Image (cartoon, rainbow, N blue to C red; front, side, top):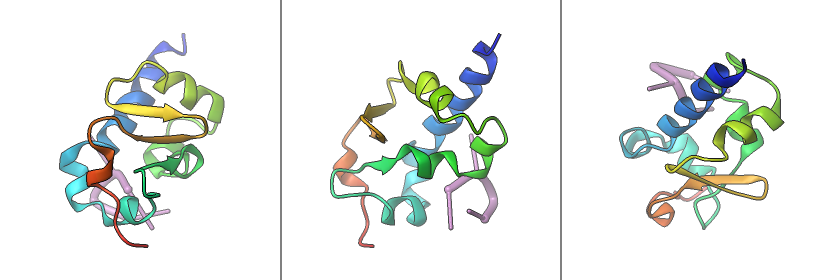
Length: 89
RNA sequence: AAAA
């Protein structure tokens, strides 16, 4: 049903938090807090996520079992060494 | 928003 849409959401967000993307993604990194977190609502505004859903609860559901990204409350970060990535605001 |  929505299983395919959730897979697309998960994979897209896992790409944003990949090392390959992060190395050059200064916008994403300058929006991180000191722990590497971004609000999920910021990620939801990225155009490829908007190209899938505007349902925030579905995004949370899609990411619940991700090994690449860590969800903490309303926030998301790369699970591995998130502190490598923040940039000054 | 050259997959912020």
